[PDB]
Image (tube, coloured by chain):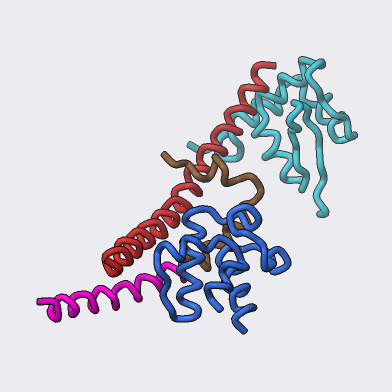
Chain colours: A blue, B cyan, C red, D brown
Amino acid sequence: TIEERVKKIIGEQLGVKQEEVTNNASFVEDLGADSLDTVELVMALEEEFDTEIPDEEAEKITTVQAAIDYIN
Amino acid sequence: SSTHIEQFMPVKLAQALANSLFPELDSQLRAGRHIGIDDLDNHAFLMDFQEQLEEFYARYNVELIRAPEGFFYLRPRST
Amino acid sequence: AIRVTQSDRDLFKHLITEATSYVSADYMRHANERRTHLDEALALRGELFG
Amino acid sequence: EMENVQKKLRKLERDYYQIREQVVSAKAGWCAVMRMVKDNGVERRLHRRE
């Protein structure tokens, strides 16, 4: 499903545990993903669901909950 | 040429085994004694010919070992 | 005392320097390839959007 | 001219897709090394920016 495909992408693009990645887990502070890591995370999220996102609306996404919210 | 020490043994190893300190040291080492910095004679001797002694004792299937603290001792192998 | 310590130091230093030279080089090679392809992708992305 | 330019745009689009896939594949592999180098080996010793 989408709400777990997001976890599939996030865990394997940041290397963090599945338990760590909750809905409210922010990438930078909780998951530790920095500038380039978050860039690669958004690219992977785009690839998984074969869609595209605007630059500003994409950069607005900075959390698992926000990630799914834009994805779903 | 023939009848020449180098045919059978390295010169430095023969030089070490011919030293007057060797029998004492050998005897002791075999008995399990550790050698530290205070017994100068022995220690110095060990230092001078380390690799030859190591190579020698290797014949026996035993390692002549040097701890970081500077002390020598014997560690036997399974064989 | 000197004769001991000097030796010890020589071995330490040689191993350290050669091992880091051996590993860090290829680690940076990988990091640089990844950086390069990411940069190309971002330039392509920006140009496409525009 | 705009229709002709939309053809260059489509070439760039296909190129961008290819590069995107390649970058993601690189990151997937590199993650394992990152989890493995958490030993404090990476901060300065391995990541020699020079």
> Is D13 one of the magenta-colored residues?
yes
Q: Residue, x 72% and y 45% (percent of image)? A: B59
Most foreground residue, B41 or A24? A24
Closest to the observer, A61 or D32: A61
Of the 4 image quadrants, the one containing the C terminus of chain B is bottom right
The residue positioned 67% from the left and 64% from the top of the image is A24
Magenta-colored span: D1-24
Where does residue B15 sit, x and y in percent of width and height?
A: 64, 25
- What predominant SS class does the magenta segment belong to? helix
* Residue at the bottom extreme, as displayed: A1
Residue A4, given in percent of the width and then of the height, sits at 64, 78
Whether residue D35 is situated above or below residue A2 in the rendered picture: above
On the picture, is A12 further left or further right than C18?
right
A38 w.r.t. B24: above or below? below
| Residue C38: % across, % down | 38, 61
Q: Nearer the viewer, residue B9 or A16?
A: A16
Q: Is residue B42 above or below residue B55?
A: above
Q: Is residue B69 left or right of residue C20?
A: right
Relative to residue B7, is residue B23 depicted above or below?
above
Callout count:
0
Q: Position of residue D30 (x, y in %)?
A: 52, 62
Most distant residue in the left direction: D1
Whether residue D38 is in magenta: the answer is no
